[PDB]
Amino acid sequence: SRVAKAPVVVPAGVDVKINGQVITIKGKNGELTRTLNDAVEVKHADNTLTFGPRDGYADGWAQAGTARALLNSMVIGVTEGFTKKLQLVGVGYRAAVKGNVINLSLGFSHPVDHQLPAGITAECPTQTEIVLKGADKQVIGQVAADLRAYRRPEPYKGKGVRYADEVVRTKEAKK
Amino acid sequence: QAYVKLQVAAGMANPSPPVGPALGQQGVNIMEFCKAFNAKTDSIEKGLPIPVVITVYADRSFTFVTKTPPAAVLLKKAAGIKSGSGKPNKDKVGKISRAQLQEIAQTKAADMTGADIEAMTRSIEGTARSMGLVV
Amino acid sequence: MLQPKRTKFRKMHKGRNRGLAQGTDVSFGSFGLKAVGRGRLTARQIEAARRAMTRAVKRQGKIWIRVFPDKPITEKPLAVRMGKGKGNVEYWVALIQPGKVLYEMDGVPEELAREAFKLAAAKLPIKTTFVTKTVM
Amino acid sequence: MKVRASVKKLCRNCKIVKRDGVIRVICSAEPKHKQRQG
Amino acid sequence: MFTINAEVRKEQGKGASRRLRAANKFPAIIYGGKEAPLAIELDHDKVMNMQAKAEFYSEVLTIVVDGKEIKVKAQDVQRHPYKPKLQHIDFVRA
Amino acid sequence: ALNLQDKQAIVAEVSEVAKGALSAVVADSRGVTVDKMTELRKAGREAGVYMRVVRNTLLRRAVEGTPFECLKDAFVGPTLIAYSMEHPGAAARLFKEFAKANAKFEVKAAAFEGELIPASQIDRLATLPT
Amino acid sequence: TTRSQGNGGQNVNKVNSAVRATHLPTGISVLAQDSRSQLDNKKLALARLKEKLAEMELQQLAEQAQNHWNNHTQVQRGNPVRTFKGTDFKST
Amino acid sequence: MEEKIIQITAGRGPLECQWVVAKVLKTFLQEATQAGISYTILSREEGDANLTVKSVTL
RNA sequence: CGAUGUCGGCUCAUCACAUCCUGGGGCUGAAGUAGGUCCCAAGGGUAUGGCUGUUCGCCAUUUAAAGUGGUACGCGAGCUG
RNA sequence: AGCCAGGAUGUUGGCUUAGAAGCAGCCAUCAUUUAAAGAAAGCGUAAUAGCUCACUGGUCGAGUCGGCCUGCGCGGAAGA
Ligand SMILES: [Mg+2]
Ligand SMILES: [Mg+2]
Ligand SMILES: [Mg+2]
Ligand SMILES: [Mg+2]
Ligand SMILES: [Mg+2]
Ligand SMILES: [Mg+2]
Ligand SMILES: [Mg+2]
Ligand SMILES: [Mg+2]
Ligand SMILES: [Mg+2]
Ligand SMILES: [Mg+2]
Ligand SMILES: [Mg+2]
Ligand SMILES: [Mg+2]
Ligand SMILES: [Mg+2]
Ligand SMILES: [Mg+2]
Ligand SMILES: [Mg+2]
Ligand SMILES: [Mg+2]
Ligand SMILES: [Mg+2]
Ligand SMILES: [Mg+2]
Ligand SMILES: [Mg+2]
Ligand SMILES: [Mg+2]
Ligand SMILES: [Mg+2]
Ligand SMILES: [Mg+2]
Ligand SMILES: [Zn+2]
């Protein structure tokens, strides 16, 4: 509703193409593409992107705000992108990368092997945290969720794969 | 930067029991703080606590400011009793005079962030009333 | 345990309580419970709800009750046929009156009143509503 | 997980949600808060 | 001071009451002293909201029935036994 | 704050602005409660307890409150430009006090515009009667 | 809930009104099959368990009074900790 | 707050021992109340003569 | 009622899932061997013995357990008695 | 509602307690600076301390909020 109300900005010289509901956006960073929900009308008038319902649709303004949020997300992605850093808290918790292949030494009989898509790459300035940047917010969040769900940590001390800005709620095992 | 005042009566040095390591939570010494407190309390009476504020800095050269003795013990000495009260609403303890309340107010007006003495005078009067030191 | 000192007779018919009721209005207290439907309030249930309301009010205010288990019902102890005469006296209840105030409260806020009456709904199988004393 | 009939909001910072037709309460302030009906 | 739009109920009765309650109308009657008894059909939620006030059974209201103001006041009431419906509301002329 | 409280407050500020002419500006964009305490204590020592540091600089509050007197504040109301009163004396020295407070560790959100009370420019008025 | 061991009839060969209340700490069990109503059988079993545990609670007081009794003959006549002399009854 | 049950008994002695038991019980109660502890009497089975108690539980 | 054979055991199992339990989702008063648990999952195990005129239960050694039942409280035109 | 911020002074109120200083519990539960402060509503420790919240200052801004009667839904609902 109020999300679709707000106007949508795009940079200058960014090749944004609309084909019905199929909206792709490409620039100096890269290309982000998806076909949008059918409950939305889209049109562009020389400086803006507007979202609204289609005639005879129940979830009209709601899905219009949805598509508004989606297109702003991919606009920011083609401008600079979104960054994530999967950080480990623990005694000797480390990892590595080979382009997009990851080893995990967190107490297994085989060090786990992980894979990332071509959209995400990782470097290792440190060996306890991995720095991996990209332009796909949902892809990098999926990578975060995957390397978190490999071994979801415990609630007692704070030992496992957590997030950069997260603070651990300490439930200490009562003696 | 770590503005926590935790001090005891100046009569006894090295307040290890009451706070102890609480004053030494950082890497600063526990003897220098006591020496500075004694140096500040040399020119005033001994046997009463004095609050001192602290902002510890890295160079092991602490900057501190002292304050007047607490108004709690001030009104304690004014009433001439050591214990405040037990269930104040039920029973009467002592009689507290407006003039001596005003004089207790004027001696700590310099410490307190109050310009008109009347407002903080009625403040301490209400404090005494709530404690059971009826005005 | 609300129960008569003496009754008119030891048993009585099972009885009927249909149609509309007469305990429509509030009589003694500020806050009450309505039961639109139909059922039965055991003496244990009535005493339990009274104790629970005392619990919630912390002995502030008063409690009131309108219906009484003055009718000692005869149910049949299990595994006995329809015959052998009427059954045996087993317990005491009162049945549910559409529009009746059952338990009453005063001296405590409306929020605590609805809380305690929902707790009456959670100590009784009967359908409820929150009522107060009517202006004339 | 919790199996009851009367599910209720737990504290000032939980969240009633609908997930596949059943009420779900979660509050990471208490890892216990994960309610359920059925 | 509430000015309420109400009409004259030609035929009364129990079946009439049931159909009027289906069609969102509940009755009331004008009386008082020596005057001729007339009875009216009221606007339900309007009356409920107006009598939710504390002054309904005290103040001198005004009734528009067949294009005329009538000054009446409360005397008595009947209510639905187990629902928020005022079975009857009573008027004494002012 | 509801409508009646707003009406009494707006009448109060109308009376205050009618009685007093001089004004000075501040803004709590980076104004800590330490700065607020310093300013309120300086006001309490300079003048009475009615010295206020309230912020009524909204899009529809100060501009709509000023028309009784000093209508020039239509350029002042918006953009978080607070109002501080200076009743006693002509050309009181509380004007430069807010500039000095801005100088000592502030974000420079006051702008020291000064409301051009002597019809002077937005710069400091270095000379005051003594 | 199990079958009442009669001789017997074909209805009691079905009835699971035999109620056995077993107390898990003490291991004491009592069976009730007096009535063909299983609620009353359960109540009777609970009451009998109450009674029978009130005879294990009652044979402990006697057992410890058998130990209180020995103290009467366990008094040793010598090495006094306190001494009272004369009717003046002075402590020492 | 501790709970102690103590017994004072004459042993297998004569009326002199019973009399001594009575006197010692009285002095014991007086000293205990002086020391500030409370008590209750459980058993006070009598002896064979006047002012002679056989055993008492405290 | 001019007849539809009962309890337990054996073979075959049957099927239920309503799970006892491993195999799989969570709380924990769940740190890790390790259990208290609220449950999905019936493909499958659902022991070996002593006592018992007898599913019931206790005991000994494994161990996931030795489920609750319809099968006319299985199955007797398959066995026993 | 998000967003930058205050959220104090008497006060470290007094007990009983092993220290209780806002948080183990009880009593008064209020006075001042009053845009704001509730002897504390949460987190915590050893006693603190500290971090919050209620409340109120600064922004996007036209809409926002809680009772009711009715139509149809949601879960309570696992067999041989
Ligand atoms: Mg009736
Ligand atoms: Mg279930
Ligand atoms: Mg009819
Ligand atoms: Mg026979
Ligand atoms: Mg049978
Ligand atoms: Mg037959
Ligand atoms: Mg035949
Ligand atoms: Mg045949
Ligand atoms: Mg488990
Ligand atoms: Mg299942
Ligand atoms: Mg199976
Ligand atoms: Mg199977
Ligand atoms: Mg299957
Ligand atoms: Mg065997
Ligand atoms: Mg053998
Ligand atoms: Mg079977
Ligand atoms: Mg069977
Ligand atoms: Mg069979
Ligand atoms: Mg056959
Ligand atoms: Mg056979
Ligand atoms: Mg035989
Ligand atoms: Mg339902
Ligand atoms: Zn919660």
Image (spheres, coloured by chain):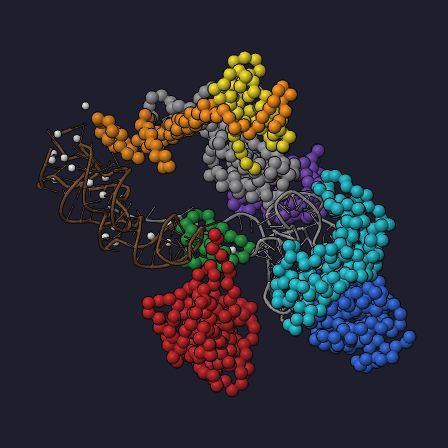
Chain colours: A red, B cyan, D green, E purple, F blue, G orange, H yellow, I brown
Which of these two is toward me, B82 or F30?
A: B82
User: Which residue is pictured at 90% across the width and 76% down the height?
Assistant: F129
- Compared with E67, B19 (above or below) is below
Left/right placement of residue A6 relative to residue E61 reads left
Displayed quadrant of residue H37: top right
Most extreme residue toward the bottom, as rendered?
A13
Left/right placement of residue E3 relative to residue C78 reads right
- Compared with G59, A70 (above or below) is below
User: Which residue is pictured at 88% across the width and 77% down the height?
Assistant: F128
Most extreme residue toward the top, as rendered?
H49
x, y (%) of residue A76? 51, 78
Ligand 18: image quarter: top left
x, y (%) of residue C27? 61, 33
User: Which residue is pictured at 72% across the width and 74% down the height?
Assistant: F105
Quarter of the figure that contains the C terminus of chain B: top right
Which of these two is toward me, G61 or C74?
A: G61
User: Which residue is pictured at 48% across the width and 25% down the height?
Assistant: G75
Figure label count: 0
Left/right placement of residue A136 relative to residue I64 reads right
Which of these two is toward me, I13 or F33?
A: F33
Residue C95 makes an appearance in the image:
no
- Compared with H10, C23 (above or below) is below
Quarter of the figure that contains the N terminus of chain B: bottom right
Left/right placement of residue C36 relative to residue F126 reads left
x, y (%) of residue B100? 85, 50
x, y (%) of residue G50? 40, 29
Which of these two is toward me, I34 or A53?
A: I34
Residue C86 makes an appearance in the image:
yes
